[PDB]
Figure 1 (tube, rainbow, N blue to C red):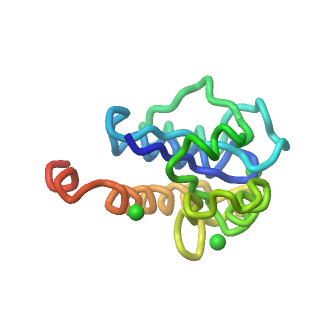
Figure 2: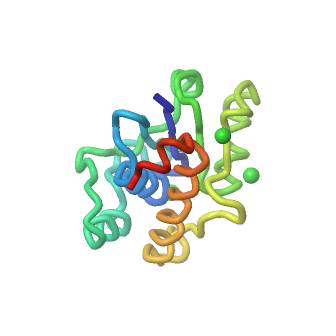
Figure 3: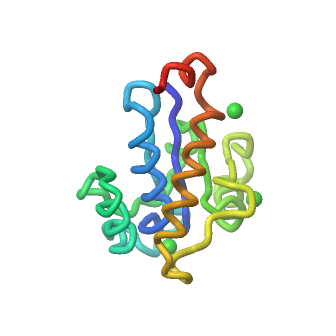
Amino acid sequence: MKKVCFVCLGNICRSPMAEFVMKSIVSSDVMMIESRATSDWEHGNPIHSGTQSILKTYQINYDITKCSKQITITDFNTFDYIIGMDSDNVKNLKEMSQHQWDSKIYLFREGGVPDPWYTNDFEETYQLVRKGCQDWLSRLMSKEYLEHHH
Ligand SMILES: [Cl-]
Ligand SMILES: [Cl-]
Ligand SMILES: [Cl-]
């Protein structure tokens, strides 16, 4: 079971969106998927309204109990892939872990995902997260898995 963690600054906008979009395209039995924040700055707060609204609009199930959670030393050891939503998340992930795990740290998509904390365009965010989740699936799953879904 591959263990994937999407990461952004506050874990209320982009990275939770990736968690639940990814969870909608691959089974809990073959991939374990969570999300985290690099910072403290939103800890305990629920998914941002813009991500919640997007997920409801596209009928993507999510855990209403989900709250912003900062990534921990345990997480860096446990997760196989720690995927930052933009290059700032990637850099901060590497420094806060003193570069001990750089080979598990990835950028979600080349060029990045625009930050809807600034653009407020959660539709653009959804479309890019949805496509990037598809790419991660083709990257992380075996060819045999790909050929039988769907
Ligand atoms: Cl944020
Ligand atoms: Cl990067
Ligand atoms: Cl790979």
